Image (cartoon, rainbow, N blue to C red; front, top):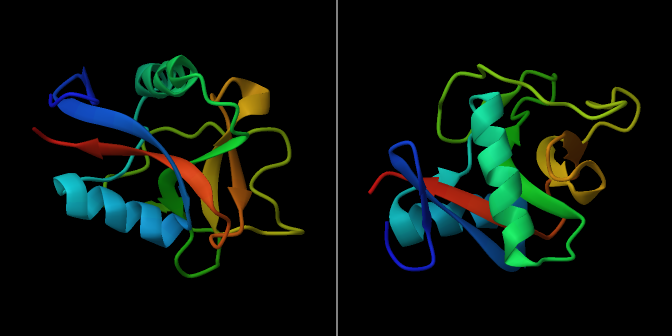
Length: 131
């Protein structure tokens, strides 16, 4: 994987401290590497991604991942199109009361759990791409 990015099981990943909307972040991932916002497909991959973010030294609270609810009916999809083989919702997520339609990793959980937030929030983000 290229400098600045880290390999994990066939893919390359990187944390970008640029705060963007969920949409723009995902586009960034597509443009720079023909990747997407990270899909977290196993517990082990979530552990890897959490450690990647922590190693950066960031003090951010929320980091985008590629999960969103495109029809606002709480049917979640990865932007990369992967199946949802793994879920790691934090306490009280996803909210049915104040639903957000995009998903972030939360520093309060070591970036191991997810929270649904407004897609128009500007958070840092992790990209995942092949090669």
